[PDB]
Image 1 (cartoon, rainbow over the protein chains, first blue to last red):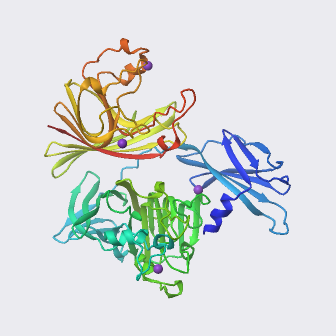
Image 2: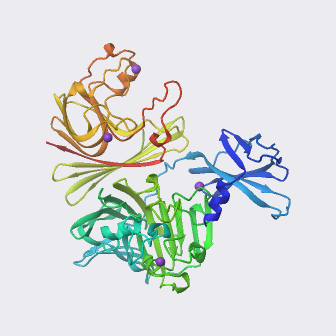
Image 3: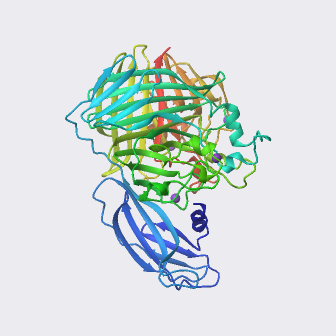
Length: 409
Length: 204
Ligand SMILES: [K+]
Ligand SMILES: [K+]
Ligand SMILES: [K+]
Ligand SMILES: [K+]
């Protein structure tokens, strides 16, 4: 995946946008742009609104101004995005006709949604037992285990949707950059993986602090709080609400506290093993290829749709892989998640990726492992033998908030 | 502030008020603010605020709440960065500790009046019978933002009835690399699009 980051950062045309004007600057020293046209496209949350093309005619080191036509105003709420691409119409000795040599995106106008969701005809029903809070609505059921404080099962009709409960996750199967030169017989205590292991991040157990249920006018509200601890040290506190309303949507609000003296964690998110295996993964967010917070320039915001296997990057030494960032909607099987998150989705658990030394030894697990992160640490790489994630990509804020809506698709 | 939603729910040990507002200008929605206020049997009011800011509006100077309190009290006591005025791009000198000053020391008398007296990184503020806890920036004084904006000279300011409190989840840098062109660096501009903050308001 890193190759596309290199291609993008090494582009030979640079772009600025001011109003309707794209300024194209050539970083060629010798050639005119005699095999180039610029394709531009504007889309509303991935729905195409307009597009066109203009030939590039820019001297080496020169500039060209391209004035976009006035766009019709979008017919609904959302964010308009401009993407431009430089396409070479003619084959060369080194490329085929249609080769894309450069791209860039910008946010254009945003019209925030102010329209209220229509009041639903049904209201969900809570059953309280010693073991569980259960919520039923039509063809859906959600079960919160009261001893664990997690969503342990959901049903659509008779079908269970979870193989493992939805739980917080603060670790990642460590990248080569997280490990550096550390080895079992010669620990490098400075490496990220060793800081996390020494602080108990991989071993920490959830302690339940609070698990309560209330009914609102139009919804059932489940409130939980957990502490992760290691040898008497509280590493992380996760406070949540789940609100399940008459429309079938479950809104999940998560507020995490991270002890200031614990090493900053690899991620702040949730995970679960879904019962289903589906063929496609469809999302509105950065893509199409794997992208991480400090390696996401090349990815573009649009609507992507790939086979599940494309969502796993087969690094020979297995690790956390396949994240996509800046995602506002994710679709898989009957499920839809909305928010502003990073995710990966695959048949391999973090545990399996961490434990397995070679990609050919991985086996697909039952169902589909989903990791959905409010926040994810950078991956680094300035070298691979000392910590290299720059401070602005470390999760050092202390308090973190994210919110997800889980509904049917 | 167009009102989108205002509801009340009576819970087990609390009343929950939920609001949503859109700020608009000439048809353009600039900001949305969604809040809950949870008032419990201990008398605490927990306020949660989630704001959306249109990506195409200029980044805002602050994202916060304000009000004019009836109370005028002698001291201001906070656990936060101080003791002097500090802003996000000018707070290295301020230290985190418990500070306790006369009210007048929470106003900086710039000859040309403007926003002034913020203290950042504050976890607890006390003023008269009130206490606010969270992780916020604040200023507190006898002068409204409107009055500071409209008044050309500090000697023309008049103390208003009561006390103006501005409590911000987030505040833009002040800049200063020069004073004739925008100078607040990107990392101190409120560009994130979505902002969350939470406060508890109680008595004592
Ligand atoms: K990008
Ligand atoms: K491994
Ligand atoms: K400081
Ligand atoms: K003034």
